[PDB]
Image (cartoon, rainbow over all chains, first blue to last red):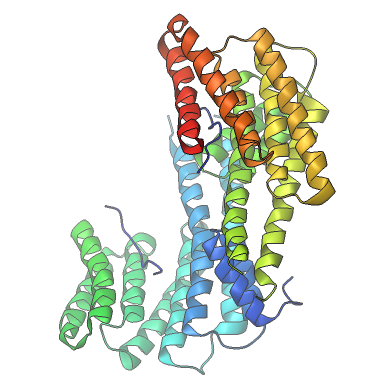
Length: 9
Length: 10
Length: 229
Length: 228
């Protein structure tokens, strides 16, 4: 786990 | 499908 | 240039390049489509964002590989020179996306969904610049990212439900900015937690489709909370 | 373009571009290395081959995806984009064939280096054949045939039947027979001979040399099952 940002679906 | 010579890693 | 090409042909070729995993071509085709000067549809906004995310994504992951090899400290100039070359390409792409947003896409016209989409994307490409910036330039860039995210948040608070996937994605990216960029973990934890809780409350109104979409993103908030707390 | 950079520095940055999966950068660094005009080491040869194989790899896969879309039917956009990708791939094959004929292919050297470069020449004419038509196709097919044939004649004379470079050459010439020259009989016949003649001498190998030879024998066996 590292900080994750919004994906693009 | 058909396979050709891969890249060699060593 | 894409100036000689029909807008409709540019959109089709953007879709072909996505299918072929040619994301640099997909981004050039979508830029041509934007420069026609008509608004993007929801589908077109997502093509534009997927193209430039893939391009800058590859560059940020290269920059971090090279920046690690550079930081291992106990030495020729080659690693530094290649890290600088990748950095300059990354900055090139962000300035291109930021020029498209300011010249063509960010307006006071349009629904909340388009207005928020474009101000979040502004906040995001300033955030990608802040990751590689130093000194006075970094400070200016951090301020530009904060103002775009804050303006996007103000609109999403007034004009969207707390479960809206665009509003959740914005709140996630803004907490990531608070934590990774602005050295403000308290503000990061507070925003992710409030955003989670406020969205939890409205989930029962949502069909199966929009339930999945809200919860996919609400989990990313909880996973960051797990990591930060 | 890479002219102002030291040869050692281009080799280092080719290795960083590979670690960063920047295969276009890696290819342009290795091209500047070749253009220094000194022979490539076995390790440098492999970095050049890796770099251009990954560039041309992405273009052939894109080209395949668009060609299949084109075949299931109609505005001109699919053909136009297929043609732009085609044009880039030809640009890269022409660069490789130019470096091979200007700098790498020599009458000097061991069998390993001379076969490695003639095989590569066959491979890049084969990639051009995959997208060619008409009179151009016929000339390209003859070019690929003559590079591979020249490489086969050296490897039969100067190399044992287990040698991985000989085996990868024979695998790629069999692919050429099946995919490009529309002779599945010669493809199966070469793959089968290459495999059987290697198996006869397998017992002479040990350690990584045994493993490297059986790696490529598996691919000959994979193609033989797919093709028969």
